[PDB]
Amino acid sequence: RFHSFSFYELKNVTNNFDERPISVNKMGEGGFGVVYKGYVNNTTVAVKKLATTEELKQQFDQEIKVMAKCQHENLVELLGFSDLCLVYVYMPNGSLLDRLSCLDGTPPLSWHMRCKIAQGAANGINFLHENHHIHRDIKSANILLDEAFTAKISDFGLARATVMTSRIVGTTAYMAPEALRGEITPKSDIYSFGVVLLEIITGLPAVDEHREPQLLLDIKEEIEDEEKTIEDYIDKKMNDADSTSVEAMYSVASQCLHEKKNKRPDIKKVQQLLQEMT
Ligand SMILES: C[C@H](F)Cn1ccc2nc(Nc3cnn(C4CCN(C)CC4)c3)nc(NC3(C)CC3)c2c1=O
Image (cartoon, rainbow, N blue to C red):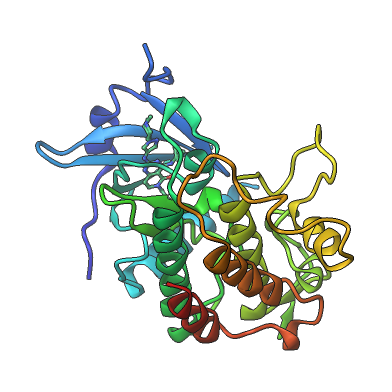
C-alpha cells in the first residue's frame, strides 16, 4: 500500500498553517481546500488544508482510495494524509490554468510545450479510463505541472468507478450538457478535455464574465458558422505555433466538444490523434 502520517506531524511543516502570500505559506486555494508549502528534509510537499461535514470527509477518503489504486507519470502523487489535511509531492510549476495566464510573472508556454502538456494530460485520462474511473472535474486548474512541465491530472474527490445522480457537481464552464443533466459517463471527461484543449490553443480561460463570448466553448460555434477562424483565436503569446498542428489540435477539441456524447471520440482515439499531430 502507501504512506500514512499523523496530524501532529503535518501541523509543524506548514509553520502552523500561516496563510501568507509567498511573494513577501499560502501558495493558492483549491476547490474545497487550501494549499501550503511544506517540507520533509530534502523533498518539498503540498498540504491540502480542507475547510456538509459528512461529504467533505468522503471527498478526502475517495482521494486516498483512487490515489492508492492509480499510479501514473501523468497523475499527481499522494504522499500522506491525516480538521483534515492531504499531502502531495509539490508540483514546481503549479497549474496549467496559472501558466496559461502567466500568473506571478511566469513566461508564456511555447506551442511545443503546449503540445507535450496536451499529450501528457490525454495519457493520464487514458490510464484513468483504462482502470474504469471517471474523473468528473477535468479542467486546467486540475492539470498540474512538474519540474519538466509534465502534465499531471489532479483532484479525485469527485471521481467515480451511463448512471444518474441527484447532486450535480463540477465546473459549469467545462461540463458536458449531459453532465449538467445529472448523467455520469467517461464521455463527459472527453468534453471537458475539449475545453482544456481550447484553453491551450487560445490561452483564454473557459469563462470570463467581462468578455464576449463569456464561454470559451462558444468559439467552436463562431468558427463553424465561418463568423471567425482559429487564427483569430490562436494565443498571441507564442512565436512557434504552426497552422498545421494548431488546426490539428482544434480538430481534436472540436470532435471532443460534440453535443451528442456517443459522437465524441474515446480517450484512446484522442490520445492517437494528438500523437499524429507532432
Ligand atoms: C489535489 C492536487 F493534486 C494537490 N496539489 C498537489 C501539488 C500542488 N503543487 C502546487 N505547486 C505550486 C503552486 N504554485 N506554484 C508556483 C509557485 C510560484 N511560481 C511563480 C509559479 C509556480 C507551484 N500547487 C498546487 N495547487 C495550486 C495550483 C496552488 C493552488 C498543488 C495541488 O493542489
